[PDB]
Amino acid sequence: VSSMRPNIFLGVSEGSAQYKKWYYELMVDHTEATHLRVGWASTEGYSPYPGGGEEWGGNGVGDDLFSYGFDGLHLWSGCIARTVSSPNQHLLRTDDVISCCLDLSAPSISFRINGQPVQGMFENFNIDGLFFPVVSFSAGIKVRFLLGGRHGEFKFLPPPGYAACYEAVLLKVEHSREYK
Ligand SMILES: [Cl-]
């Protein structure tokens, strides 16, 4: 299991914050046991290093208390699966488009699948740190972030009040993979 993320970091501050609600999509270009989870993680989940260093771990989305993932059937956090429902329900597969929503004002993390709402969302979790889009996947799986911006246009309209993640570009994708 590998992971990818863009360099987009969203969070609370004491400055101007016209947008507290953030949206992106993931397109699944190819799927062939397997793993494919998408959602968000916080920098509070970084691994500590000597001298105060903190590093992204690149682990499975929802396999700790700092990340929040959807796989088509379940929501994941803290290594535990919650069952959710949707129309036409399936584990993620080729040509699925997953919408990911982060509402820092609620707080909530919620999803759509091929434009339809997933019934069940994350609530009652902390919003310490900065949040980033993130996906994790087993071998051979091909996915793309659609962040907004001319090279990653959305397939669906963001919900009212939501901003494209591309607007928070202060754009690169990082991929973490096992070495061995
Ligand atoms: Cl890979």
Image: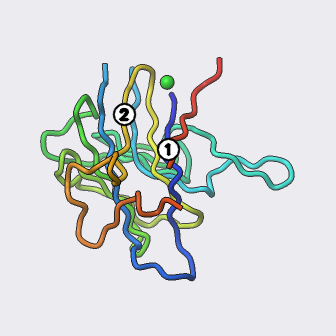
Which quadrant of the figure has residue 13?
bottom right
Outermost residue, left direction?
88
Element at label 1 = strand
Circle 2 residue = 143
What kind of residue is marked 2?
A: Val
Check disc 1 and give the amino acid type.
Answer: Arg
The disc placed on residue 24 is none
Q: Is residue 39 left or right of residue 171?
A: left
Give above or below for 160 relative to 18.
above
Residue corresponding to mark 1? 5
Query: In the rendering, at what x and y percent does residue 53 appear?
Result: 78, 51
Q: How many marks?
A: 2
CB atoms of marks 1 and 2 within 8 Å: no
Residue 106 percent coordinates (x, y)? 39, 73
Task: Locate residue 57 relative to residue 100 in the image: left or right.
Answer: right
Which residue is the extreme one toward the right? 51
x and y percentages locating residue 86 in the rendered image: 18, 47
Dot 1 alpha-carbon crowd within 10 angstroms: few under 14, some 14 to 19, many 20 or more: many
Please rate how many residues cluster around mark 2, counting C-alpha atoms within 10 Å: few if below 14, some from 14 to 19, many from 20: many
Q: Is mark 1 within 8 Å of ligand 1?
A: no
SS at circle 2? strand
x 36%, y 33%: residue? 143
Nearer the N terminus, badge 1 or badge 2?
1
- Residue projecting furthest to the front: 150
Q: Quadrant of the C terminus?
A: top right
Relative depth, front residue between 151 and 177: 151
Figure check: 117 above or below 179: below
